[PDB]
Image (tube, rainbow, N blue to C red; front, side, top):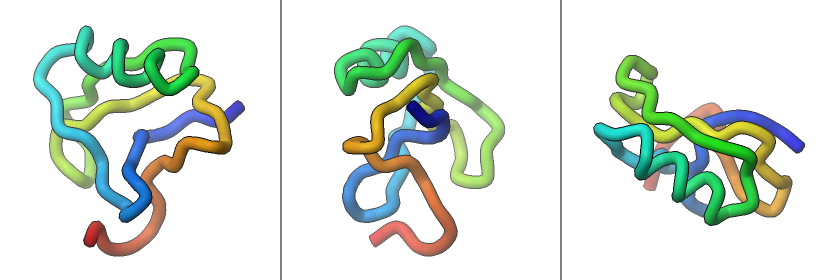
Length: 64
């Protein structure tokens, strides 16, 4: 469906160092694939491709 940085129900991304971790995390959540992006406005977090609407991605605002 959509692409972006997988977040949790409280607007928080997931930290990473390796692409494998993000890949599994993303696939675990029905995505196509995933990779760790080292330079993002939130730090080094997971980015997913073709992630379903049931799963949230980061949006504008705070992580609480």
